[PDB]
Length: 66
Length: 132
Length: 40
Length: 315
Image (cartoon, rainbow over all chains, first blue to last red; front, side, top):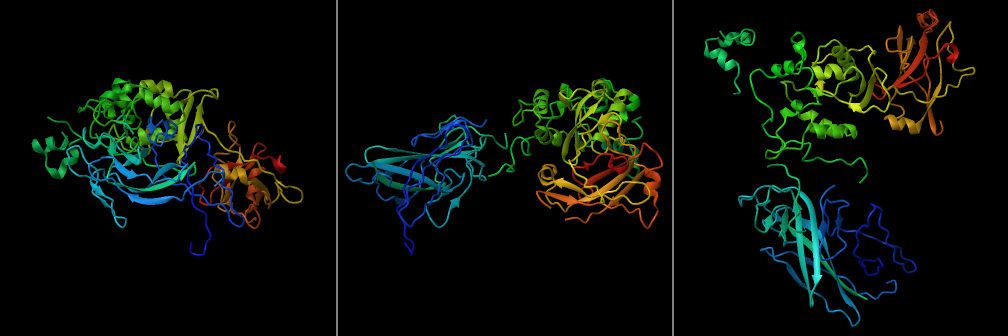
């Protein structure tokens, strides 16, 4: 695509687990001569901080701000 | 990709129609042995609730937040946005909620309490693909 | 979000004693004495 | 986002508090209340210089009642909680910046110089009753140029809870500059004098030294631009409690010219040569005198960093 060789973008639905720890997602194995790319984009959010469970694609539990 | 078979992701520009009713988007037909996936991501938004038209990719109409007396005021401040989707018989049913400052919205209606339910003041990009 | 969602929000006499001093005849040119001497 | 991120809010901001007050509005305000909690009429000039005791419900009469439409949760309990939790910023933004009562506008946390006056006024019975007792001993919140400090009156233990019994008028309450009652927290940086045939503090000439400061502890006290500096040298009897020569018999400002490793160094050369020798003629005119070096920002601002009050030959 426009002189650059690319692989198709593939997607996963992710939320952070308890502990406020960074979320680790394993990088896809790139073919010989290509390097990994990544982008995170906002889907759902609230200001609950730790008082929430957004892991269901169909509903969002938001219990308010600490 | 990493042992799993996938189809290319395809994208659509979506807005809710006025009336606060959920958005119906048809699920792509998946090859035999693969299952449907869906994701909605935020493009444009405001706290206008029902007083907006984001259906144009090139401009955004935002008329402000609904006040308790029904009149149109300024845009209230925002606290959260939820994008929810459920696949049911070849149809992805999309629901949304925009969280704004309370004590501004009327007691009843589409935009009430602290929530703008399935608002027109929201544009999301719908991605579909299949995987095993 | 369910209907329990709630957020913070931004929203939910005065001429004493100088009026009295003028009313019982103190001139505005010398109103500085209004707080220095009591009513009769 | 990094930890310096901060935002506006609805709880310690404007637009919430309305033109109302849970206290009684009358024509004997605020002097009737001042006398009623024990301020003597002989010292009623302080009625507008110091607030009602933060320990009593009357202090909070100024705010809209917590049950009326739109009021912030402001009570003597919420005040004490934030106080003992160390949330001094929320106190400044939620309570202090919005007190605005007793016909006085410049309400602030007392300075170290102002607590010194408050202790003298408390002992002399010139305050309200609850504060005439409160400022006798204890640990008190102070604030100098946007910086919080705890001062100690009477040498109380270090684990005594922090006390902010009242806020004061920034300019109306006159501070006392002498350090007697309220003992502060002066900072002494770990520094090496290189000595040898270099640093010299002996009678008969100019005093020169060459110190060396550490970068990591300069950045802890607001010194990251290691050339935005200036130096002061003091001569006299240091304070018996903190060690600073607060009123030196001889004060001298000098500017440095140094440029090494994971630390940076700075010089110092007194101008005692080619003018009056009198630095050594007063430093060594009394055996109890000592020489102390102080570091400030270029214009005299910043956390004051002090060296030891040295005897002859840096002893």
